[PDB]
Image: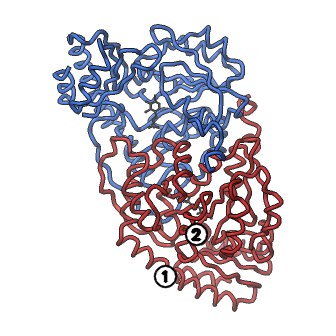
Chain colours: A red, B blue
C-alpha cells in the first residue's frame, strides 16, 4: 500500500490559549503587483526590521514565521541519522517536531526546579549535537534565562554547535534580548516573530538574527520565494516607525492587564501557585487542574492545559487578553 | 569555523522570462483577523479549488506554491541517503534542487528527441526510486506528454513509487489534465498553482491533488500554518465562480497572442526553429542564441536562456506577454 512507501519516521509521527494579541489591528494592501514573483528577501521588511532590532541588514533573514526559522537551522546544520538537536523541557514543542519530521535525533536535558538551565547535564550531552534551542523568556513557564548561564552555554558550544535563542516574546522585556551579543558570538542565532506582541499571527512572518556567515548558509536552504507579496507589504507597514510605536503601546497595555490578572489569581482558592512571567501569558498551578480546565472549557473559556508537560502537572497556561476577558476567567474561577 | 559545521551537501549547494501573466489583477483584503493564527488548511480555498478541479475536498492540499508541494513529496517518501528521486531532463529545475538540499539521490533519464519519455530507460533505473516527477506540459519545451506513455509509467511504478504530474500550466490545455485518473491510480499525485494562468505568482499559493491516503501522509509533514490569512483570503476570491471565469478569459487572450508570436517568429531570419507549445511560453532555437540573447538584454527585453540545458543548445524561452511586448521582441529580432 501507499503508507508502506512512506518513511518510517513519517509513518509514526474566550480564546486565551495560543498567546495571540486579543484584538485585531487593521491593515490594507498598498502593492498591487500580485502577477509577478516577489523578491526572495523583501528589502523593505529586512531593512525596517534591522533598524528596529538594531542589527545590520545582512544579519537578518525573513521566513514564514519563527517556525520556519527553527526548521532552517536543522536543515543547514544537522545530518539526518548522524547529528543531534538539544532542547530543555518543559518548553516550545516545535523543536522536537521539526527534528522528528526531518529525522534528526533529539537530546533533552530538562531544566532545574526553577526552570533554569542544568549546565552540567548539558555539557555531558553535547557530543554529536549541532544545534541547541533555548527559549527565553520560556514558553510555557514565563521566565527569562539567567544571562550568566547563557554566557556559559555559549562558551561550552564555541566551535561545536549553534545556539539558538528563541525570542518570540522579547517585545515584553526588550532589555533582555541577546541581539547585542552577536559581535562576541559567531555561533549565536536569534528567532523573532510578528505573531505575538506585533499582533500579526495571521501573517506567518518571522526572522532569524545571526552573523552574516550563518545567514548565508541559511539562504542556501530556504525556499526561493518564502514570503508572499501581501505579507511583505503589511509587514513593512507594521515595521515602520509609527508601527513600532503602536506596537509598544500594545505591549504596555498587555503588561498592565497581566499584572492585574496575577494579583487577582493569587486570591482565588483553587489557585495553588502563580508563577512570574515576562510575557503575555501566565502559568498557574491549580488544585484539580483537569476539573477546572474542563469546567471553563464548557463555559466557553479556552485555556491551554500543560498538565502533561515535564514538571508542570496541575498547571494551565492563561494568555493575557482584554480586561473583559480577564474578568470572565476570574469570575469563572 | 561556522561553515565547517554545516552539512556537506549544504556547503556545496520587458519581462518575458518567468512565465508570469503580464498584467496585474487587483485584489483587496476582506478578512481583518490578522491577530489570530490561520486554520492549517483554509476551508474556503480547499473547497473552491476542489469544485474547480472537479475532485473531492479530501483530495486537495494547499501549500506555499507547487514548489512546496515538490518538497513535501520528497520529505514524506524519500529516506535521505537511501531513496532516490527520478526526473527527465530538460525540465523544471526545482525537482533536483529540493532533493539535493534535502540530501536525496537524483536519477535522471533524459527524454527522447521529441521530448517524450524514454520508457525503457526509466524502467531500467527504477530500483530505489520513491518519487518520479513529470512535468506535462513540460517547462521549458512546451509540449504535452503522450497519455499512453503516462499509462505505462503508472503501470511500471504501481506499488513502488509515487508518480507526480506537474500541471503548473494545465489551465492552457485543461482537457489534458490527469485529475480524472485518481480513481484508477492510488500512487498518482498532481501539482497545481495559482502563479501562472491565475496571474497570482505573488501569492505563493499552490495545491497537490492526490488520493486521501497520500494527502494524509503529506499533512503529517507540512508546517502547522503553511498559508497566511491574506493569501487564503485573496485565493478564495480568485477561486470563486466569477474568478474562474475571469481566469479563462486571461488564458484565451494569452493563447491568441501566443499564436501570433509563433506565426511572426517563424518568419524571422535568425530564428531556426519554433517549437509548438500548449502553454504561455515559446521555446525557439536561434542562430547565435547568445549573441541575440545579450542584444535583447541590452535593449531591456528579458528572456530566459536555455542554451545550457540538455538538448537545448541555441534555445531561448520566451514568455507570452501583451501585444505590445510581442511587438517589441519581433521588431528587436
Ligand atoms: C509563537 C512562538 C514561535 C513561532 O512563531 P511564528 O512566527 O508564529 O512561527 C516560536 N517560539 C515560541 C516559543 C513561540 O511561542
Ligand atoms: C511555476 C512552476 C512551478 C511552481 O509554481 P509555484 O506555485 O509558484 O511554486 C512548478 N512547476 C513548474 C513546471 C512551473 O513552471
The quarter of the image holding the C terminus of chain B is top left
Q: Chain of mark 2?
A: A
Q: Position of residue A138 (x, y in %)?
A: 66, 70
Q: Does the rendering let one see residue A25?
A: yes
Task: Look at mark 1 in the image and give the residue it sits on.
Answer: A253
Q: Position of residue B97 (x, y in %)?
A: 54, 32
Q: Chain of mark 1?
A: A
Residues at discs 2 and 1 in contact (Cβ within 8 Å):
no
Q: Alpha carbon of mark 2 to alpha carbon of mark 1: how far?
A: 24 Å
Q: Position of residue A78 (x, y in %)?
A: 69, 46
User: Ligand 1 is found in which quarter of the picture?
Assistant: bottom right
Foreground pick, B141 / B104 = B104
**Callout 1: few (<14), some (14-19), or many (20+) C-alpha neighbours within 10 Å?**
few
Give the foreground label among 2 and 1. 2
Q: Position of residue A247 (x, y in %)?
A: 44, 73
Foreground pick, B246 / B318 = B318
Residue B34's label in the rendered image is none
Amino acid at each position: 500500500t501507499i503508507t508502506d512507501l512512506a518513511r518510517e519516521n513519517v509513518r509514526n509521527l474566550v480564546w486565551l490559549n495560543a498567546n495571540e494579541y486579543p484584538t485585531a489591528v487593521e491593515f490594507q494592501l498598498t502593492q498591487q503587483t500580485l502577477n509577478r514573483y516577489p523578491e526572495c528577501q523583501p528589502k523593505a521588511v529586512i531593512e525596517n526590521y534591522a533598524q528596529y532590532a538594531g542589527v545590520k541588514p545582512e544579519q537578518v533573514l525573513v521566513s514564514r514565521g519563527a517556525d520556519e526559522g527553527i526548521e532552517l537551522l536543522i536543515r543547514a546544520f544537522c545530518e539526518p541519522g548522524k547529528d543531534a538537536i538539544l532542547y530543555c523541557p518543559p518548553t516550545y514543542g516545535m523543536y522536537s517536531v521539526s527534528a522528528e519530521t526531518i529525522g534528526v535525533e533529539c537530546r533533552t536535558v530538562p531544566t532545574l526546579d526553577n526552570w533554569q538551565l542544568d549546565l552540567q547535564g548539558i555539557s555531558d550531552k553535547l557530543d554529536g549535537v549541532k544545534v541547541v534551542y533555548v527559549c527565553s523568556p520560556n514558553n510555557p513557564t514565563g521566565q527569562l534565562i539567567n544571562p550568566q548561564d547563557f554566557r556559559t552555554l555559549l562558551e561550552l558550544t564555541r566551535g561545536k554547535a549553534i545556539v539558538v535563542a528563541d525570542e518570540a516574546y522579547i517585545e515584553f522585556c526588550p532589555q533582555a534580548s541577546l541581539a547585542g551579543w552577536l559581535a562576541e558570538y559567531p555561533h549565536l542565532a536569534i528567532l523573532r516573530t510578528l505573531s505575538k506582541a506585533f499582533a500579526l499571527a495571521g501573517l506567518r512572518c518571522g526572522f532569524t538574527l545571526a552573523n552574516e556567515e550563518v545567514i548565508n548558509l541559511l539562504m542556501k536552504v530556504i525556499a526561493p520565494y518564502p514570503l508572499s507579496t501581501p505579507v511583505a507589504d503589511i509587514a513593512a507597514q507594521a515595521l515602520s516607525p509609527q508601527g513600532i510605536v503602536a506596537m509598544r503601546e500594545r505591549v504596555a497595555q498587555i503588561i498592565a492587564e497581566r499584572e492585574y490578572l496575577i494579583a487577582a489569581l493569587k486570591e482565588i482558592p483553587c489557585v495553588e501557585q502563580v508563577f512570574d512571567s515576562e510575557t503575555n501569558y501566565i502559568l498557574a498551578r491549580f488544585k484539580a487542574s483537569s476539573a477546572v480546565f474542563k469546567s471553563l472549557w464548557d463555559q466557553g473559556i479556552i485555556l491551554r492545559d500543560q498538565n502533561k508537560q515535564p514538571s508542570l502537572s496541575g498547571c494551565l497556561r492563561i494568555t493575557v487578553g482584554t480586561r473583559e476577558e480577564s474578568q470572565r476567567v476570574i469570575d469563572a474561577l
